[PDB]
Amino acid sequence: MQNDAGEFVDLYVPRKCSASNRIIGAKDHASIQMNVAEVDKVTGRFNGQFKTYAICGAIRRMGESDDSILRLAKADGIVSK
Amino acid sequence: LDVLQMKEEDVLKFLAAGTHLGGTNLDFQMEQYIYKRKSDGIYIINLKRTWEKLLLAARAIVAIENPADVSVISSRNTGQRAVLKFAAATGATPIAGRFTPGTFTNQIQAAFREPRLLVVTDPRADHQPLTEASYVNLPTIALCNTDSPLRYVDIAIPCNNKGAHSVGLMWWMLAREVLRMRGTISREHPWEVMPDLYFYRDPEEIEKEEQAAAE
Amino acid sequence: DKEWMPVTKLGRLVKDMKIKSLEEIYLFSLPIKESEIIDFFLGASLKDEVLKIMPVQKQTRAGQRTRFKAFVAIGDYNGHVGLGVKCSKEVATAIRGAIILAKLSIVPVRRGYWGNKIGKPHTVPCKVTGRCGSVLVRLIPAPRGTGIVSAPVPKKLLMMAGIDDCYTSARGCTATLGNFAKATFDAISKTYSYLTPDLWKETVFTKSPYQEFTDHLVKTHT
Amino acid sequence: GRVRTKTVKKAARVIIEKYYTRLGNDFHTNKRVCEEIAIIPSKKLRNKIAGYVTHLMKRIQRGPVRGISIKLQEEERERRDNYVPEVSALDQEIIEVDPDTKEMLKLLDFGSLSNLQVTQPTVGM
Amino acid sequence: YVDTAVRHVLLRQGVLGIKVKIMLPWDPTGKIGPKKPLPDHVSIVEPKDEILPTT
Amino acid sequence: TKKRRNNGRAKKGRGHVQPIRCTNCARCVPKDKAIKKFVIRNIVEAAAVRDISEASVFDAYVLPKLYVKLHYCVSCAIHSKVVRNRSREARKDRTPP
Amino acid sequence: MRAKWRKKRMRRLKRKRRKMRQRSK
Amino acid sequence: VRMNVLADALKSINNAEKRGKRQVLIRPCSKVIVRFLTVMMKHGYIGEFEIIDDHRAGKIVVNLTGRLNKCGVISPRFDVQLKDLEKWQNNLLPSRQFGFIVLTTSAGIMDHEEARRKHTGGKILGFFF
RNA sequence: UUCGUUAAAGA
RNA sequence: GAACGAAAGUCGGAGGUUCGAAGACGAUCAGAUACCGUCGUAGUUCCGACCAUAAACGAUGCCGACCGGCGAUGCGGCGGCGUUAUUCCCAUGACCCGCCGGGCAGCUUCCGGGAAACCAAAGUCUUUGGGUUCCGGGGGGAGUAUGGUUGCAAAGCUGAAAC
Ligand SMILES: [Mg+2]
Ligand SMILES: [Mg+2]
Ligand SMILES: [Mg+2]
Ligand SMILES: [Mg+2]
Ligand SMILES: [Mg+2]
Ligand SMILES: [Mg+2]
Ligand SMILES: [Mg+2]
Ligand SMILES: [Mg+2]
Ligand SMILES: [Mg+2]
Ligand SMILES: [Mg+2]
Ligand SMILES: [Mg+2]
Ligand SMILES: [Mg+2]
Ligand SMILES: [Mg+2]
Ligand SMILES: [Zn+2]
C-alpha cells in the first residue's frame, strides 16, 4: 500500500497462492509452501537452487493441490514434456 | 532430463513387483493417472506418470536441509517393515506402529517433533497425520491407490499399496533416487543388496523351513 | 527471570535471534504455541482489558457446580490485537488463562484510508464482515477524525486495534459478548484475507527461517 | 484375585525391562532377586510383584510380549530382519500379465520382450 | 505424612475455621521429612551390566 | 426436531400406502412402516426331531417346514424384544447377523 | 386439554349459540 | 424461464470464483455480456476469453485469474440520474478507491469512472470487484 | 391384572 | 374465477359377510360410562347429488442457471468376434461393463448456509437484487363475536375489538 508520497505503509505483504491466486491468511494454518529443487545436466548434480509453490488451505482441503502442482510445474517444464 | 528416463531393468522390476495393477474403484483425481480399464475389475495404472511423481517426491525429499525434518509413517505391517529400514538408511526419521494421535499437536509429551516434510504409505490407514497436517503446516507424499482420498495431500504416487512387493519396490527405488540426487550412489552404479528387507518377510514358519531346506 | 526451557523451535529461533520481527512470522503463518514469543517481540502490547467474567453452571447430583468464564481482549495500539476466552473454577486462574490464550490468539490488523492517500492510516481498507453465532458485524471505512460509533466493547477493541475511524453495523443478539466480540474479531481478522487491489504482482517468495538457519537448529537440537 | 494394580504391574514391567538375566522361573529365587535389585517395604507387595514377575517369565519363555521386549529378543528381531537370501527379489525373465500393458509397451517405448495374449470374461465383482 | 492444623479466627462476622494440611516430602537422611517411603512408590536402581563377554 | 430422515416409514415417491394389520395388537400400520419379517421354523422342536424320526413310518423321507409372514408394529415390537433402541450413530446400520 | 377437543367444544358452543339465535331471532 | 442472461452468466462466474476453478462455461451470448466482460478485461480482473460462435447462440469461455471477489447484476436496471451515483457508491462498492459499477450510458456500455468524465450517466447493469 | 394426589416460595 | 379432492358426515335407490360410532351387558378398580370380553344400530359395500376439511407433510411455493464424489435402482437410447436361449448365418429375449436424458432415493465431505438439529439444498445472503404468487409481526383472547357469502344440515371462506 502506497500513499501520495510513495512510502510503503503496509505491515506485511502476504503470500499469494500459486493455485488460485488467493491471499493466504495469517491464521490459515492449513497452508503450505512446497519446495522443489532444480536438477542439473547428464551428470546429475544437486543444486541449491529451488522453486517455491504456495498452496493454500481450501485448495489443500478440496484436493486441488495434487492437480495444481503438476499443472503448475508443466508450465515450468520440470515435471513432464 | 535425459538421465531420469526409465530403463529396461526398471520396467522389469516394476512388472515383477506388479505395480501396474491397482484397485477396482475409481477416484475423481485418479483419472489422469489411470490409462485404461481392464476386465475382472482390476484397473491399470501407467508407469511414466508414476515415475514422474516418484521423481518429484525424491526432489522434495532431497530439497530438505535437515534429514531429521522428514518423518515417515506407516500403520499397516506391509509398510512398517519398509519404514524402519528406509528412514534409518539415508535421510529421514521413522515412526510406525500406533501413531499416538495428538503427536504433532501438544508439547507436554516428549514424543513431539517438527517435521518439515511427511511421507505416508496409505492415506486411509494414515488419516490421522493427514488431519494433523493442518496444524503443523507440513507437505504430504502418499503412495496412493485408485480408491484413496486426496485431502491434505501434495504429491500422490499412484500404485497398489496392498501387495508388499510393490510397496517395498517403491520405498527401495525412492531411496535409490534420493541417494543418487544426494550423491552417495552414482547414476552408473547398481544397488548392492536385493530389496527383500524393504518388501516383507513371512515369520518363522516358512522362514525356518527355507533355512532348514537350504542347510 | 525464569529460563524459557527451550522447546517448539520457533522460540528457539527467537532466542538464537534469527527472526527479527513478528511480521516475518505472519508472512509465513507459522503456528505460535507459547505466549512468551509475542512478549519477546512486543513489550508495549500489555494494554488489555477484561470484558466480562460470567458464571456458567453444570448441574450435578450434589448441586450446581459453577466455573467462571473470563474474556480478555489484549493488544498494542499499532495493529496487533487478540481475544482470549477461558473457563476455570478460580477467578484469577481464569483471568490468567484468558490472558495467555489472547496472547496465543493475537492477529494483525490491516489499516487503510478513506480515499485520500496522505498517510497515517486510520480505518479499515474496505467493508468487511464477521460472523459468530447469528452476530453479523460489518466494519465500514470512515472519514478522518470520525471516531468509532459502536458498542463500548468493540469500540475498545478497535481502539486497541488502531482503527481510529470506523462505522459498525451489527445484526443479531448483540447482547451476548461471547459472540459479538468474536464476530468483531473475525471482522478484523478478515482484513488481510480480503483480496485487495494493491497486491497484483507475484510476491518475492523469501526463504523460510528454517531454511535460512537450519544449521543453528541442528546444533541446538543435537 | 490376580487383578493387580497398575503401579504393581508397572513396577514389575520396569523390573523385567531393566534386569532380565538376573531373573529365573522360580518364585523363591525371583523374589530375592527383586528385593536385591529394588526396594519394596511391604512383604505382601513383594510377593505380588514377584508373582507377576514369574508370570511374565513364563510368558517370555513361551513367546514374545507386545508390551515390552528384551535386548535378546531385539537382537533376534534384528537377525530376522537382516537374514537376507536371494530367492524371490527378481524372478526368471519370463513375465506375462496383460494385453493392456502389452499395448503400453507398444505405444510407450520400452522392451516388450515376452508374448502377451490372454482373454478374460467380464465376470468381475 | 500429612501435618494437619485446625484453627480459629475471631472476626466481626463471628468465627472462621481454617484447616491447613501439608503432605511432607520423603527424606530418609535428615529431620526434614519422614524416613518411611510411600507404600505406593516402588524404588528401582540403574542398569549395571557392561562389556567383556568371553574373550 | 425431526428424529429421522425417513420419518419412520419408506414412503418417498408415493403418497399413500395401504395398511396391513399387526399380529399382536391388531393395529393397521402401513407396510413400509410395520416390522415385516419372515420366520422360518421347523414344525418340530429339535429334541423331538429324534423322537419323531425313531417313531416315523418312513426312514427319514420327509422334512416339513413352516414359513410365516410375521407382521408386528413398532408399538408392540419394542415391548416384544425385536427392535430395541439404539444410539444416534447406531441408527445408520443394516440388518444384524 | 387437547386443542382438538377444545375446538370441538367451542364448535358445540357455536352450534348452541346459533340455535339460541334461531330460537330467539 | 430464461431472462437476465447477464445475471445467469455472473452466477456461473461467481460460483467458479468461489470454487476456485480456471475457466467458466457460459451458455448465453449478448453484446451486453461481451461489453461487460470487455470492461472487466480492461480493468484486468479476468483474462482472455473465447466465444464459440454457435449458429443459434454461442458459448463464452473466460480464462479466469483467481482475482474476483464478487460480481452481480442489479435486477430491475434502475434509471440513475447524476448526483445520485454516490448512493450506489456507498451501497455497492466496498471502499472509495476499489471496485467499479457498470453504467449503461447513451454512448455505449461504460464504467463508473468513465461516466463522470463522459458526463452522461444512465441505467446500471451491475457491479464487480 | 389394579396401584390417584402432595400449596407457595426459598439455593 | 374454475376442475378434482382421503376418511368421516348428509339426501335418494339397491343390500347387510366381517368390523363397528352410539347402546345393552359381563369383568378390574374407591368409583367407568374407559382400556378387556359377548351381542349389535348408523356406518363400513355399489350407483347417483352435496359438503371441501386433515399431521391433505418434504411440517420445506413454481420456473431457470451454477456449484464435489461414490455405488446402486426404475424407463428409453447407444457401444461392446462375452454367456445362455429356437433350426442356422438374418432380426428380437435373459445376464455382465460403460455412457447419455430426465425420476424416486442412499453414504461421505470444511462447497457454503444456519441457533443447532440438519441440508447437494434449507447453498450461490451485509461480498445483501434471475422472474413471480400467498402469507408472520410477542403469547392468550381467537380462528371468537358481529357482518357478508356457500351449503339440506353438520358446517366451510373472510374476520376483529375490549381486556
Ligand atoms: Mg436480548
Ligand atoms: Mg420427542
Ligand atoms: Mg398423505
Ligand atoms: Mg385431589
Ligand atoms: Mg368420501
Ligand atoms: Mg344410504
Ligand atoms: Mg368393545
Ligand atoms: Mg362383533
Ligand atoms: Mg345418527
Ligand atoms: Mg387447512
Ligand atoms: Mg402452491
Ligand atoms: Mg437398460
Ligand atoms: Mg428390442
Ligand atoms: Zn402390536
Image (spheres, coloured by chain):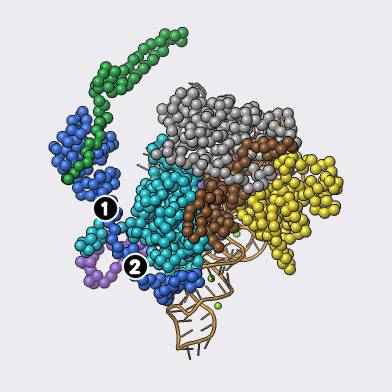
Chain colours: A brown, B cyan, D blue, E green, F purple, G red, H yellow, J orange
On the image, the x and y values in percent for residue C79 come to: 62, 32
Residue lying at the far front in this picture: please name it.
A43
Mark 2, secondary structure of its residue:
loop
Badge number at residue H29: none
Q: Quadrant of ligand 6?
A: bottom right
* Separation of marks 2 and 1 at Cα, in angstroms: 25 Å
**Where residue F2 appears, x then y in whole percent?**
53, 47
Q: Quadrant of the C terminus of chain A?
A: bottom right
Q: Which residue is mark 2?
A: D91
| Amino acid, disc 2 | Asp
Q: Residue at x 70, y 38 (%)?
A: A2
**Disc 2 vs disc 1: Cβ atoms closer than 8 Å?**
no
What residue is at 47 percent from the left and 35 percent from the top? C12
**Residue C174 visible within the image:** yes
Circle 1 sits on which residue? D79
The amino acid pointed to by label 1 is: Arg
Chain letter, disc 2 residue: D
Q: Nearer the viewer, residue E32 or H17?
A: E32
> Residue B38 or J133: which is nearer the viewer?
B38
Q: Is residue H84 left or right of residue B96?
A: right
Task: Count residues near mark 1 (Cα–Cα under 10 Å), then give few for <14, some for 14-19, many for 20+.
Answer: few
Residues behind callouts 2 and 1 on a single chain:
yes
- Residue C15 in percent (x, y) is at 48, 32
Using a 10 Å C-alpha cutoff, classify the residue at mark 2 as few (fewer than 14 neighbours), some (14 to 19) or many (20 or more): few
User: Residue J6 in the image: x percent, y percent?
Assistant: 59, 57
- Position of the N terminus of chain A, as image quadrant, is top right
Circle 1: element type: helix
